[PDB]
Amino acid sequence: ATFEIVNRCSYTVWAAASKGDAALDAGGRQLNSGESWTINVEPGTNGGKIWARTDCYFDDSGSGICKTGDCGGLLRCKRFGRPPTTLAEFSLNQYGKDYIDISNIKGFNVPMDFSPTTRGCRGVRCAADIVGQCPAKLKAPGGGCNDACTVFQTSEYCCTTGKCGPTEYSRFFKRLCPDAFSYVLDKPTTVTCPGSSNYRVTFCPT
Image 1 (tube, rainbow, N blue to C red):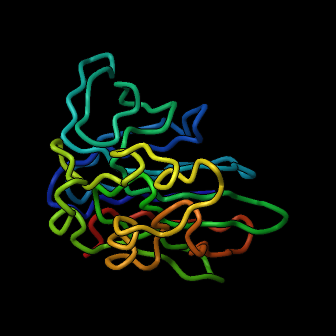
Image 2 (spheres, rainbow, N blue to C red):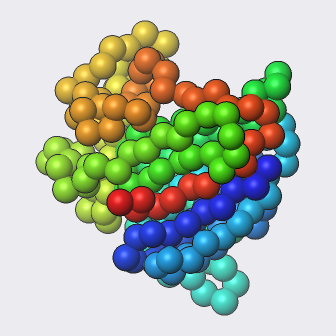
Image 3 (cartoon, rainbow, N blue to C red):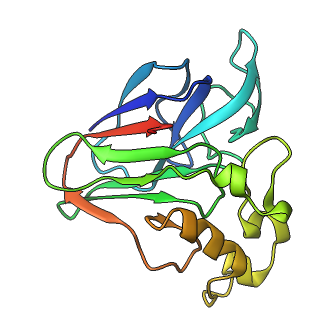
C-alpha cells in the first residue's frame, strides 16, 4: 500500500512510521513545509502508526532528539514515539478490509488529516487548536498537549483494568476532535476501507 505523507504546516516536521517493533519503509524523514514523502507499507501490516515529530536535532548518523514524538533518539524510527503525538493508526488487509483511525490517546502535537486516495471510504481529521486550548495540567513544556494517562498514570486514565469511563480530560480531546479516539474505551471512530487501499496523511490540513 502507498502512503503519501504531506507536511502542510508552516514549520518543519520529522515524519515517522513504525509498527512498534520495526520501521515502516525508511521509518522517518525530515519534511520541510510543503514537502511530500511517499512510503510503501507491506500488505497485511497490523498496528502501524504514522506521526509527526517537532523540534528535532539529528547528527550525521541519524541520532538526536525531538521535543515531541521522539523514538529513542533515531531519525529512522523502529519503535513508537514519546507522547504527545497525534496518531494515524492503521491495520491493512485484515480479512479483506483496511481499518484506519486517528487517535488522541497518546496526546496531540500536530493537527492531522488521514484520508484514502482510492475509492470506497471516507477520511478522518483532527485539526482543532488542541495545543492552544490544552488544559493547564496537560500542557507539555516541549510543546503539545499530553493525554491524562501519560501525565497522571492512574488505572482510570490508562484503563489498565479494562474498565474505565470518560474523564474531564478525555472529554476535552473529544469536544475538539470528535472523530478521534479520546480514551482507550471510546466509542470507536475507526473507518473501514477496502483491502489494499492507498492513503494520504496531511499534517496541518487547514
